[PDB]
Amino acid sequence: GTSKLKYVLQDARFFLIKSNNHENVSLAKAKGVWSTLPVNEKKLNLAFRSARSVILIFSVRESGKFQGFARLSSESHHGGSPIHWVLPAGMSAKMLGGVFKIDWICRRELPFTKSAHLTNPWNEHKPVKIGRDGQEIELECGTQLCLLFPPDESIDLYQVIHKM
Ligand SMILES: Cc1nc2cnccc2c(=O)[nH]1
């Protein structure tokens, strides 16, 4: 069902995550972590303290799809075991040092063709698939985008509701 999902998404904030490669999203799915550039790390930390749920919606460049979405369960933290991200050119491990813990809400794909009717007011009302890494998605657009994903029956949202 979709009712617990709607409860998790109620008054959430939503951010677009754009990865150049599939390997980093697969690591994030396996380890429940994500790291981003400092300019976005600061925005996510502010958002984490400001809202019941902060949702990251992931898309791999050139894939034509979103790969899933997840909820921040912590602010960024430093000093843990290094995650072996595949680092894009011009991006170093020191730049991705801040690690957020995330709980996946959906690990299934959504092709851009299914989200063509959704535009993001915070990016000039361009289709929601369009945006730089870290682009915030307005509440209604983001909620409808997350509801478009096929249900992920492997996930039990009871545990993430308790974290709100
Ligand atoms: C973990 C990580 N991977 C990426 C891959 N491509 C572009 C940006 C990123 C990023 O901010 N973080």
Image (cartoon, rainbow, N blue to C red):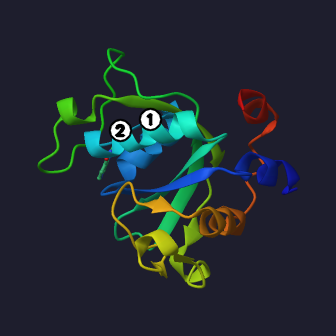
What residue lies at 79% left-to-right and 54% top-to-bottom? 6
Q: Nearer the viewer, residue 60 or 95?
A: 95
Mark 1, residue position = 45
Q: Can residue 128 be seen? A: no
Q: Is residue 66 visible?
A: yes
Q: Give above or below for 31 relative to 25.
A: above
Number of numbered discs: 2
Q: Marks 1 and 2, Cα distance to the nearest angstrom?
A: 5 Å
Residue on which disc 2 sits? 42
Which three-letter amino acid code belongs to the residue tagged 1? Answer: Asn
Tag 1, which secondary structure? helix
Q: Quadrant of residue 98?
A: top left
Q: Residue at x 39, y 44 (%)?
A: 43
Location of the C terminus by quadrant is top right
The spot of residue 132 in percent (x, y) is: 33, 63
Q: Are marks 1 and 2 in contact (CB under 8 Å)?
A: yes
Give amino acid for label 2: Lys
Q: Nearer the viewer, residue 161 or 21?
A: 161
Horizontally, residue 149 falls left or right of residue 151, namely left
The percent position of residue 62, horizontal first and vertical second, equals 35, 71
Question: Residue at image x 74%, y 51%?
Answer: 10
Mark number displayed over residue 106: none
